[PDB]
Image (cartoon, rainbow, N blue to C red):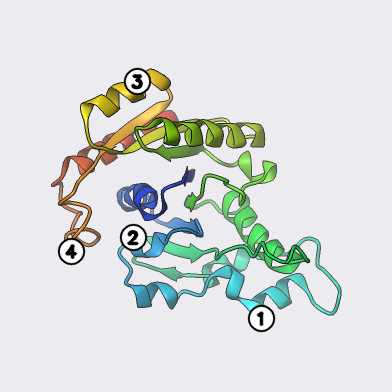
Amino acid sequence: MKLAVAGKGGVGKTTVAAGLIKIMASDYDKIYAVDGDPDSCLGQTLGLSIEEAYAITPLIEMKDEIREKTGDGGLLILNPKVDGDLDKYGRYIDDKIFLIRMGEIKKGGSQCYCRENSFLGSVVSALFLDKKEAVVMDMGAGIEHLTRGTAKAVDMMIAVIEPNLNSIKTGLNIEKLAGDLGIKKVRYVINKVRNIKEEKLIKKHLPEDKILGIIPYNELFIELSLKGEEIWQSTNPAFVNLHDIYQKLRLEVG
């Protein structure tokens, strides 16, 4: 089970990936929760406190590891071996979920951050190609972490969008970037659906077969201090839809 959750909505969208991971934790013996979204924090949305999350050094910050894996002194190791060291690049949030933080990819300068990028690329490659454990990687709409080499291992690309033309466009694009990349299955997940009018708008610009499910908005079940740790219980409707979405997912892949 190799899953990729892409969307342009920060924490809100990442909550979907987080939710799927928590549900999958009851079926899989081990899950690699990969935070590849620079404008979000899969760790916190998964229950970790600010300090617990930061205590988990992101790949981009593992200077010594980067030096050892990619080389140094003007020499670059073309094919880095890290598959066996993955379990050292993160922490077990619990007895099932293992979180790995990618870290923001430095764009400025345009000089040559090959070493860092190489280390991150090698980790993503191992996670999707060399590991047998379930993988759920959260990422932005650009999905730049994925390549045609790892796209083949992706069981499904889930595009999380909102019920509005603006977000619908972003979704259609994510479906394109993923499609042209190699990913065979791309499904949608409508998040923050507040009204029926928004639902009709969805069933208008997207086919029922491409929609994995819908997640209703909760003003008193997503904010305040009742979100995060308190959700294991089947309370808000968003919980019921998450499961149905999961079942739809398992049916697609299985």
Q: Which residue occupies 35% across, 65% down?
A: 44
The residue under label 3 is which amino acid type?
A: Lys
**Mark 1 surroundings within 10 Å by alpha-carbon count, few (fewer than 14), some (14 through 19), many (20 or more):** few
The residue under label 1 is which amino acid type?
A: Asp
Q: Which mark is residue 46?
A: 2
Q: Which mark is residue 64?
A: 1
Real-space Cα distance between discs 4 and 1?
Answer: 38 Å
- Select label 2 or label 4 by which is in front: 4
Q: Earlier in the sequence, mark 2 or mark 4?
A: 2
- Select label 4 or label 1 by which is in front: 4
The residue under label 4 is which amino acid type?
A: Ser
Residue 222 in the image, given as x and y percentages of width and height: 22, 53
The residue under label 2 is which amino acid type?
A: Leu
Q: Which residue occupies 59% across, 32% down?
A: 176
Q: Which residue occupies 71% across, 62% down?
A: 118
- Select label 3 or label 1 by which is in front: 3
Give whichever of 50, 204 is nearer the camera: 204
Q: Which mark is residue 225?
A: 4
Query: Which residue carries the number 3 mark?
Result: 203
